[PDB]
Image 1 (tube, rainbow, N blue to C red):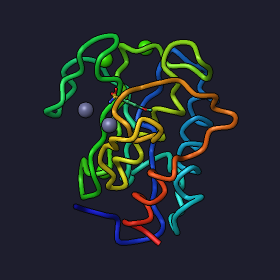
Image 2 (cartoon, rainbow, N blue to C red):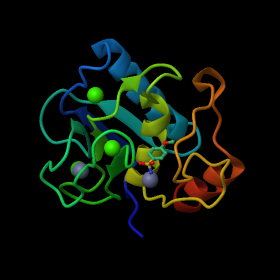
Image 3 (spheres, rainbow, N blue to C red):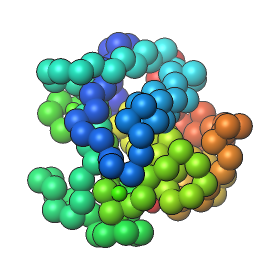
Image 4 (cartoon, rainbow, N blue to C red):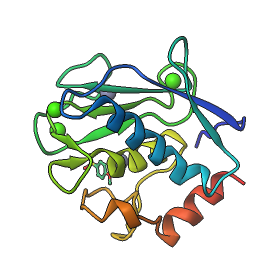
Length: 158
Ligand SMILES: COc1ccc(S(N)(=O)=O)cc1
Ligand SMILES: [Ca+2]
Ligand SMILES: [Ca+2]
Ligand SMILES: [Ca+2]
Ligand SMILES: [Zn+2]
Ligand SMILES: [Zn+2]
């Protein structure tokens, strides 16, 4: 499927979850992009205005695409594969409780997964992989991509 055909990728944070400190939202998203730029030729920059490649949105229920959210639990987030317009965009369910830690749903960990989709990755059948469909908390301070995630992303880039 689709991949970004350029090395400098931009992201924009459309709006901020009230569940977290603003600076923590910013850092969790930055860190999540870094996971992917660590293992590809990609470079990601936050822009504050105008059109980004990847728009990060928090929203609940019906929010203007074809992927209605479902309240607390169930689908936590979803994102669009590379492409123009909504392509690349990552949407986080406001009905989750977003956090920096193991409480609620960890924003960083979810963002690593969603950004994987934003870059062109589908789900992994390997429970060890970040791209495995089921959310399971792992220590964010020592987080590492599975071998499965690395071969997947490296099949698309670099
Ligand atoms: C690790 O990150 C995630 C993010 C989302 C989901 S899901 N498919 O909405 O339950 C699973 C894992
Ligand atoms: Ca949900
Ligand atoms: Ca986009
Ligand atoms: Ca919330
Ligand atoms: Zn959406
Ligand atoms: Zn997914």
